[PDB]
Image (tube, rainbow, N blue to C red; front, side, top):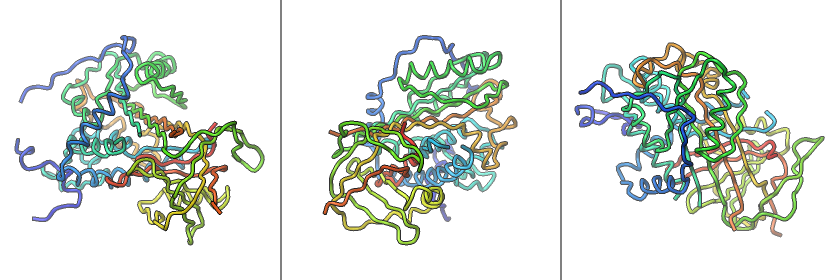
Length: 418
């Protein structure tokens, strides 16, 4: 009779009303020669979605947007507490897709936990009250698509199994809409953890192309499945240019480090929060996407501001005043960040959600002990091609926000850009 505000994330009456044993396969060795994946061709498969989207589908985009964002903030709060000096960066859509991916490979106990965790209710014992994971991932593909229609967004999934663990094809096929660049590979995750922990990094360097050095504090030696999501965003922001020479960046009252600064001029929106005192600069990247850049009143107030502005479901601090003449100067960002999602779940006191007693039967021949669940982000902001000027010379906050879907694609903190 009635319907939830996230109603389009559920199984529909036709698909739920609508069998062979599941085929399976052992992933090839990590050594196997793998050609690089063309980042340009990926954009097409994003673009192909957005250009054929309907009015029925757009509602989901926003519905998944709200959830993914809320989850983003929960986990950025866990990242904040967990950890320092480089700051942080987090992609809520990627973080969301990772969770839904685990849902799509999870059976009854873990499934509903993950569903309700994401925010879609489970009135237990129904199928039309179960999450249509595949609908969601396509809907997430929408938000992802809208970000890049110049902006680049490649996301590739590493699915590193143990030697003997066969992955079920119907599960790996579920991840399609999340990304076509899924690489199931097999290796010894027992004898030597670091020699293998390198092997993944040397494999990513090959297939993805991106130098993403990501130190591991402690790797568990008894793990069968690794689920690593690697994302790469690259923003050549229009109206901005590289500046000659390297300029200093005040990292701390004592010391600083001279780095490249990109600068532009335009009619940007700019305000200063009456309540909490932080400057905000709303520089639009494309005709939709928006880079929000917050600076605190002073360097030491940043901790508070971050806890206040980002780490909250609300974006009530985002306003819209009359634009003005501004010469913005910020560092040429090459932000890199990496966090094991298991550690964040643990800091949120959900360590058993994907623990050793997690039921992920749908993933393979045997129940996989999912060791680490990486999220890795290379976010680059490069050059595109009276007048009071906003110069980001000290630590600042930033978020990259999509208007049409309403989703928040990246948020983070720049304490030091090398």
